[PDB]
Image (spheres, coloured by chain):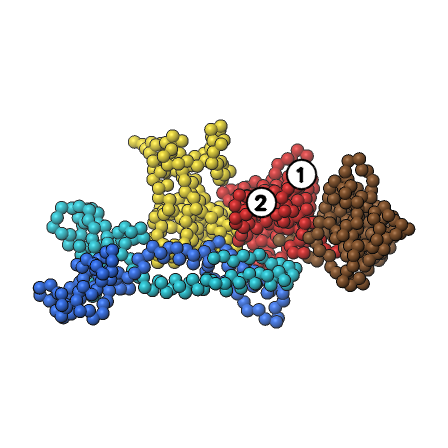
Chain colours: A red, B brown, C yellow, D cyan, E blue
Amino acid sequence: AIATYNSHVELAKYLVSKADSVYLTIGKSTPWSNETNPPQPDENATVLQEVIGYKKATKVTLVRPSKSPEDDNKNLISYGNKSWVEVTPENAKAEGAKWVYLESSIVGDELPLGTYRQVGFVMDLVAKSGISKFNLVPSEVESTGTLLFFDNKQFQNRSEQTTAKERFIVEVDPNS
Amino acid sequence: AIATYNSHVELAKYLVSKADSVYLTIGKSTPWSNETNPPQPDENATVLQEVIGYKKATKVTLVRPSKSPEDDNKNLISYGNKSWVEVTPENAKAEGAKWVYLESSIVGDELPLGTYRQVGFVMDLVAKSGISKFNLVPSEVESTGTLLFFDNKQFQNRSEQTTAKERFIVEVDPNS
Amino acid sequence: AIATYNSHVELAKYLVSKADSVYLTIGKSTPWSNETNPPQPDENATVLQEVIGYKKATKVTLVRPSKSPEDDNKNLISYGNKSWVEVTPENAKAEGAKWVYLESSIVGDELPLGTYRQVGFVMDLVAKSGISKFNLVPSEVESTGTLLFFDNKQFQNRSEQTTAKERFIVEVDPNS
Amino acid sequence: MALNFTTITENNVIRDLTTQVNNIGEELTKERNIFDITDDLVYNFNKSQKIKLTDDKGLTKSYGNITALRDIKEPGYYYIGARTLATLLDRPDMESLDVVLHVVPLDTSSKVVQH
Amino acid sequence: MALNFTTITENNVIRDLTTQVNNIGEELTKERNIFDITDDLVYNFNKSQKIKLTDDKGLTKSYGNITALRDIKEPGYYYIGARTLATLLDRPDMESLDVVLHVVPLDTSSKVVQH
């Protein structure tokens, strides 16, 4: 049988509730076949290629696309050629907020400086004892947790001035 | 923008973890337009059409579609024009068990008598204080919780001597 | 003989009064000799190398480094691993604000895509042919005005999704 | 004017793809759509004063570097500060002061009246 | 501004049709899309000098074959040739030379100041 639209809203409320455990991860530090045109991602992958490291999520919330006037007293966002609105977990079913917004930034050199092409977000990441910090290379990690989402992107460099902001808007089922 | 197959496993685990708060519900005491060939169900529902009542789940488990040879030594089920095998929560990613099995049985007039054609399951169902019993009509329920899954069936007739078993097998994304 | 702190403050109020004529510029789309280690910037320069385009300053203001407790309730900005506060022209000598914040974001492809290494800010820039828009390629600049401030970074990449926010904090005498 | 659009994926069913194509088609074909308003603007535009007489703020036009006041031939109004006026080969015989020059067009660009 | 479009054929699957619909929708809904820019043109063209004061090259406006200088009541600049002026009913008592008329607008189109 099918899943309902409100089931997807309850499964997004479960994902947003996990926020403190959520980490960005970056990988694929060597080239694709075409660097302007990466391949589409493999949903059966548990981990990135050529892993560089992990950074905790700076922002986690439900969202939906924004519209006026009814959102003009709420929390707006901008992403991916549209405006969006943060939905608070108690309103989720009323607003229909099946979408999770995920964001982290690698500020400068807090992971090894170089290039990446894969961006993902993991949850239930467990660091080794005595390592509470939010920026991690693969040897500081006791378990990488579950890779919820990832994308194959065009490459990005990192330097001390640059802040490498990476974010996604996603839903547990893109249509059904 | 997509989910991953293992996200669907971690979402099936959550739905099975709730099992004590899970109830069957039954409804549609009046005909379909074709009683041999029921219509597709409506995902936007929050409760059954023509509610008769609610009964506590007798069996909740993960499952997957069965295959020889590797399932030949396991606990098999026959349902929905397919064969299935039971799975435990700690085996879920190993088996790929993104499917939940749910079951309860309504014995005679422990809920009001007649025909029924809808079947559904709800979690987080809370009874009114001083009510401890596992069979509930819609008035003894303080909160119906959330209707997770439901189906439309050919009609079955209930009398004091009849045990109406009802059950499902379902996943969180059957088509992406 | 010497300038004074307050001279620098009043000169910063002068450069802030110019703000509307201020544009980000990006350039050096081909490699350095070492891409990890650029050459140090030459202040006799008048324009960036291999110019990719210009973008109007989305922000220009007086700022200073933040100080506690008296800034703990103010308009904080985060930049280059440091925390800063906005200041207003008529208060600049009371706060000691001799620093100018300069910023512009190149959204996606609103300048031609591909790598850049140089980042600069120009004042007195004048565009061709009555053009209104705030993103300019070199074939739409009439007078480049004056290259005020620039840096020779490592490379970075730009794609349709990624915004390239480039910015500086600067003073008229950083070092006497 | 504004379209209301939602981006579509693989198993958004054909009805959803149809809904967006309908939203697009309706906004581009309603009464006083974007095409009608733009044909109105082209029409009201060609009756306009093609060329500057002031700057964009209603102040005097800028000029290039000039050897003489007889080198400003374009029509409109121009400010000239005393320090510039004291460097032009055909300045009037008068004390150096700030001025405004009004250049009046004629039958030919080569000829003008200057106030 | 520009849409990227490719005409869809029988070789194209429901994915490719979905991609061209997403292309159309995204271009028509981007920040400062076609609709926004045309609403800005309607708002801002309403403070231009909507009526010509020169010709399109920055010379004097043309006129029709008038009877008297008082017949040119529209504002702007008008070269008049000596031969023309010599036959006007209201011409000043002076040598017929080529002249310019500047017309200055007032409260009504039946009145003007003429220089």
Q: Residue C46 location in percent, x, y?
A: 36, 49
Q: Residue E66 location in percent, x, y?
A: 19, 69
Lateral position of residue A55 relative to residue E42, left or right? right
Q: CA distance from mark 2 to mark 1?
A: 29 Å
Q: Which of A130/A56 is in front? A: A56
Give the numbered dot on residue A86.
2
Pointers 2 and 1 in contact (C-beta within 8 Å): no
- Screen quadrant of the C terminus of chain E: bottom left
Q: Nearer the viewer, mark 2 or mark 1?
A: 2
Question: Which chain does tag 2 point to?
Answer: A
**Of helix, strand and loop, which one carries label 1?**
strand
Mark 1 neighbour density, 10 Å: few (under 14) some (14–19) many (20 or more): some
Whether E30 is drawn above or below B16: the answer is below
Q: Which of A82/D91 is in front? A: A82
Please name the residue shown 39% across and 55% down the image: E43
As drawn, the residue found furthest toward the right would be B161
Whether C9 is drawn above or below C115: the answer is above
Q: Which of B112/D114 is in front? A: B112
Type of amino acid under label 1 = Ala
**Of helix, strand and loop, which one carries label 2?**
strand
As drawn, the residue found furthest toward the top would be C69
Give the numbered dot on residue A127.
1
Lateral position of residue C47 relative to residue E78, left or right? right
Mark nearer the N terminus (2 vs 1) = 2
Type of amino acid under label 2 = Glu
Please name the residue shown 18% across and 56% down the image: D114
Please name the residue shown 62% across and 44% down the image: A91
Lateral position of residue E57 relative to residue C111, left or right? left
Q: Is residue B36 visible?
A: yes
Please name the residue shown 23% across and 67% down the image: E62
